[PDB]
Amino acid sequence: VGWAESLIGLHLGKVALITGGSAGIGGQIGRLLALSGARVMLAARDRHKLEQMQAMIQSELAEVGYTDVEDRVHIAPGCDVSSEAQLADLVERTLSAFGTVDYLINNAGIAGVEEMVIDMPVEGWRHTLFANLISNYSLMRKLAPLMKKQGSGYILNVSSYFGGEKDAAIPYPNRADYAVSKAGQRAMAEVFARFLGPEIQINAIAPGPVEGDRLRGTGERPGLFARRARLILENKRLNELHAALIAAARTDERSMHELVELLLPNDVAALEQNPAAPTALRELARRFRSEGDPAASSSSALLNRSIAAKLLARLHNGGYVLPADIFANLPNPPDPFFTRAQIDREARKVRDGIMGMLYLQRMPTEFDVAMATVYYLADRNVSGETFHPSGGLRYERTPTGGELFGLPSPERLAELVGSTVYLIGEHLTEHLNLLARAYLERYGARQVVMIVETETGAETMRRLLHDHVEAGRLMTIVAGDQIEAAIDQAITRYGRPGPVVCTPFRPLPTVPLVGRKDSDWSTVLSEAEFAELCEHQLTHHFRVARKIALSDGASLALVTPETTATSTTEQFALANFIKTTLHAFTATIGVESERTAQRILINQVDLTRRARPRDPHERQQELERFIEAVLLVTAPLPP
Amino acid sequence: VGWAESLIGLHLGKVALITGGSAGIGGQIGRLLALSGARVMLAARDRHKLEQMQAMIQSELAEVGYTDVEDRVHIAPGCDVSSEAQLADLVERTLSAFGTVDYLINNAGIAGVEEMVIDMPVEGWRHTLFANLISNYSLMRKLAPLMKKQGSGYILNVSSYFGGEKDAAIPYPNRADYAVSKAGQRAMAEVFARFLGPEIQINAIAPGPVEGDRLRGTGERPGLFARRARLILENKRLNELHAALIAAARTDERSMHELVELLLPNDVAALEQNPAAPTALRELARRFRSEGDPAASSSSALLNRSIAAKLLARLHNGGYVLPADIFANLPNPPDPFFTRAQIDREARKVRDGIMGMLYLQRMPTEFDVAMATVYYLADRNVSGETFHPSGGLRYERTPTGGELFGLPSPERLAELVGSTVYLIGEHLTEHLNLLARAYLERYGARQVVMIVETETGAETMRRLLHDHVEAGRLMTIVAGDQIEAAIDQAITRYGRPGPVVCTPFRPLPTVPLVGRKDSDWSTVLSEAEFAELCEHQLTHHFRVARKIALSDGASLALVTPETTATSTTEQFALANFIKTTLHAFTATIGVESERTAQRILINQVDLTRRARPRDPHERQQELERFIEAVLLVTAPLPP
Ligand SMILES: NC(=O)c1ccc[n+]([C@@H]2O[C@H](COP(=O)([O-])OP(=O)(O)OC[C@H]3O[C@@H](n4cnc5c(N)ncnc54)[C@H](OP(=O)(O)O)[C@@H]3O)[C@@H](O)[C@H]2O)c1
Ligand SMILES: NC(=O)c1ccc[n+]([C@@H]2O[C@H](COP(=O)([O-])OP(=O)(O)OC[C@H]3O[C@@H](n4cnc5c(N)ncnc54)[C@H](OP(=O)(O)O)[C@@H]3O)[C@@H](O)[C@H]2O)c1
């Protein structure tokens, strides 16, 4: 009896659905579940790879002695998990093949946009959330009614170390969309376990780095390490150019338009020697020539067309005026822009740092991780947890949820005199009133710009703040679903902000999170409502942070939802879900912002104490602690 | 092929040592490791139970088809893990039987003292640390040199949910010694993994509540639930008596001596009707008669001899003067003091609450936990982690390591005027100087009592604080290893404290935590040095907290070790070990203190930011943040 005999019978009688099941970790989970007696459905996009994994597993089952192997491994091609229609067709296909699903393995996880937040299109961020997070809720919502009806089920989200930990965030620079989606997979397990129990287990796994094609690549496409290496070099050029232009603009009278025109020759030596160029650009050109590889055209040309478009988008998004065609006639540098020597050097440094982080100084294989996971899936007695099948890393984490604090120093508070404050929100009218009055009346801010969602919320705040509106100290802008343009309007008409307090427009929903055993679940939080929760409680803050991180001098506070004595226990859960998931965003953009030209601070203030009222005195002291917390992170630090 | 065939070969070639291996979870781990091919040594105290487990396992191995089963299961009787001499004999016995140990399963875990901190003898606390925590380091220190020499090994500490989580404490009222030992088992794994890798894995497991004799009991001895139930009733009587006497003393001119004499008739109805008794004691007697079971003598008698001795010890330890024989002639109430109906009612409430905490509303068996653990032990790719083989609980956790804070309000600071401050410490002379001067010069405290360890430390602080010593504002007491008597001296001579800041006497050691592969490890932190670390960095704070929790009006800050730019990476690790382990103490005594008559606040201030210097300005701002942090938790809250 060989190694697969430790598996025989382990999951006999189980039906498992594995997304991303045609390769990688999910391929090996589907393989090993099938060897252990489960009937499996493998879902992914490319038909050919699914058929090759299906034939490999079926062949292996027969070697072990199973009969009718065609009934034990099924495939669902064309299934992009980011498409809800496909997820509905997946469930229909799986139930018709096998009946009720016991194990939902939410394994598919796209790498995402792989850009800094400030270069990350809003739609790409949405696509990552749909593929990696919203799909996990969508499949659970479709399969959990059947699991609960039969009395048993298991939902397993494949998260990551870069989704953080129960009480600590871990930044993942250039991967904020991925990190947030990973963190949300874990938070789903932590907050939904109490509702899904006793019948249904829900846990996450969070592997450390895994040896396979995703990290290492193949003979055709570069893996995560090589892509990260080239991006290190690309973004080094973009960040250095962007930073130098911002600095040069600080002490040159020419416009950003005219400074960018100095780059049009795209000639490194000609810019170093151009006596009419500001010295920040000439020292940059000297730097490119000194540190660069003489065989790379990046060492003799400033830009390529792709980096030029990223630069222009940053300048446009940070309020500068330049024609869209400014880079149309830019000479194209001859290939290669960075050589293989540069890229491979950076790739080896990426892998060597990661191996140095691991306590064990070795990565598991995809087979190793799947094996640990398939043993873990036999444990009937744990729910709400994150299992680490590999790992142990020296990465720096940021503890979340510190409870005690006071006011900032008198020195930092005096710097608020004369400042411009942006407040963003709609639902939390009492917080918004109190904050505006604290900035204007207590700390001598010049003005507050109150950015709301609707005209009705505008009128609510104008009424609450009627005296400051009349004195011209409180301005209201109606953002709708165009918050970027509203921030542009504030900047143009009232000036750049110091403090920016970003509260959600919308409250949390008040619907059930699970259905009664014999119900149709029709009142339970729907798939589209979960996408809406993400839009209003995550994407909202991301969009504001994306713009405000280009606004020099701003200090940004991201405020997560409130829960009161009125709030249902489902609202408490969803607030804790959002807290944990957003902390992954906040920690990540914090690290990226240190590398940006712009001095901007980004912090998170949580209104829900995760504790779950006694007289309006305790109410007014809970709100006063909120004011203190916001001031603690929006008062500037005197240089 | 049956269920044990999923185990055949899983740990073939491994030698495992399981402490507490004759029953419970450790018995099942030893059983299941032996079925999976490992040779096992089972260690525990009682010879008979070890022989019965050995014969059961050997018999089962033979049923499965192993030969020479006598070579596969060995026992080590007489091994109390709290005795270092026994641990040395255990290792010698195991190496001679099997050669090198691959798996150290630190499973033995005594329940401990099972009292509130204020009723917990210092020696019992020490015994729990020796049995449950110091023994884990001791066996690792003896076995890790051989594991590292052969290139592989595994250390598994059996911790608990009530050891908390990486970044959050979980209180365990009446079990502070056990909770601290559990938390230290986890912290050992988290901080030692980077040093023990790549050759040696070290993780913890933390089961939730487990179905077996430990929780449920047997037909002879009561299990954890029944003991907890009786203790609920006993301690309810003790706490209520203690509280009423303290209150009665607040408004009666008689001494505590004379008030306690009112209890000597031990007659509930006679005290309710005694017109000479203070009303707090008469309302207590009325309460005992109203809520009590008429069949329990607790409803007609005030005390028994055991509760009387606990009461007297609390009064003596809180500074009151009473003769040791005051309860010598106390009439003994006839059995039963609490009936079976009362105790069983409380036991059912204990079990029902626990089952309601579990998301899954069911406990694993000892077999289930061992099975999950034995699968986990095959995972070669994770170190430094805590695996939860069962669990998912609704318990409230306290996040640790919040980073941002300011000063407390002006209102709380003004209440420091005229206060008496106790500072405890020796090594941290700069912190102690700065704190004393902040209390005396900035906030108008009446006086500081500086409690040091040695005459040399006394003279150091007298020199640093020479002006305040001359003005009579700074008093020094030399505690030696008698910190309780030193606190008694402060109280008698200078008055009760408001703020009490407890810093460690000793710095952290500067020795290696692991040895080079071919070394003898003789310079590595020794077994006795690890016990010393616990004495100086845990037991120190516990002893102070034990006394100060009886001092009305005190606010206690427990300060964990400092790490600077000088500090080695081993010191950084040991500081993080102590931080995590002490937070379990701080969170637990905080909950017990809410139930004590005495209004005392207990908080923890961590000097090591777990981050790992730029000019004395950053130094003076790091120390100023320490001052702010200490003030934030020692300034009283105005009523
Ligand atoms: N690799 C690591 O080091 C690591 C570490 C921690 C966590 N994880 C997590 O582990 C999970 C699996 O990772 P992996 O390394 O196995 O990734 P991978 O190798 O890139 O996954 C490949 C599989 O995912 C499928 N897939 C890709 N995009 C998809 C989409 N939009 N819809 C449906 N299926 C899709 C692929 O098939 P098609 O392309 O044909 O659709 C293929 O079946 C992920 O959730 C990842 O976040 C990985
Ligand atoms: N039970 C739970 O719900 C639970 C939950 C979480 C964690 N845990 C942890 O799991 C571990 C095992 O727990 P358990 O429920 O199996 O405990 P248990 O049933 O009380 O353990 C009994 C075993 O421990 C031995 N033992 C007791 N005191 C000892 C000492 N001073 N030295 C050496 N051996 C000793 C006993 O033999 P002798 O009496 O003959 O020495 C017997 O072999 C413990 O570390 C515990 O903290 C338990």
Image (spheres, coloured by chain):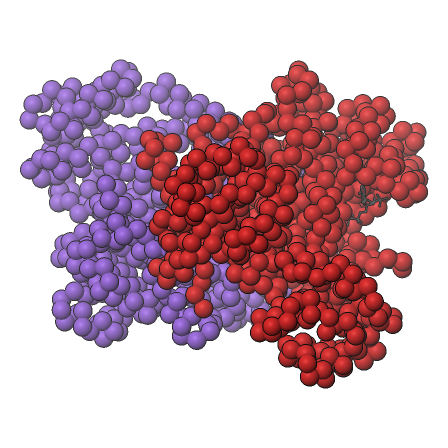
Chain colours: A red, B purple
The residue sitting at 52% across, 53% down in the picture is A494
In the displayed structure image, the side of residue A527 where residue B631 appears, left or right: left
Residue B8 appears in which quarter of the rendering? Answer: top right
The answer to whether residue B132 is above or below residue A292 is above
Report the front residue among B270 and A597.
Answer: A597
Report the front residue among A531 and A471.
Answer: A471
Residue A370 shows in this picture: no
The image shows residue A602 at horizontal and vertical percentages of 54, 54
The answer to whether residue B251 is above or below residue B41 is above
The residue sitting at 13% across, 38% down in the picture is B250
In the displayed structure image, the side of residue A440 where residue A451 appears, left or right: right
Report the front residue among A64 and A254.
Answer: A254
Residue A366 shows in this picture: yes
The image shows residue B15 at horizontal and vertical percentages of 66, 52
Quarter in which the C terminus of chain A is drawn: bottom left
Residue B143 appears in which quarter of the rendering? Answer: bottom right
Report the front residue among B604 and A64.
Answer: B604
The answer to whether residue B281 is above or below residue A621 is above
The image shows residue B547 at horizontal and vertical percentages of 26, 49
Marker count (numbered): 0
The residue sitting at 13% across, 66% down in the picture is B472
In the displayed structure image, the side of residue A482 where residue A366 appears, left or right: right
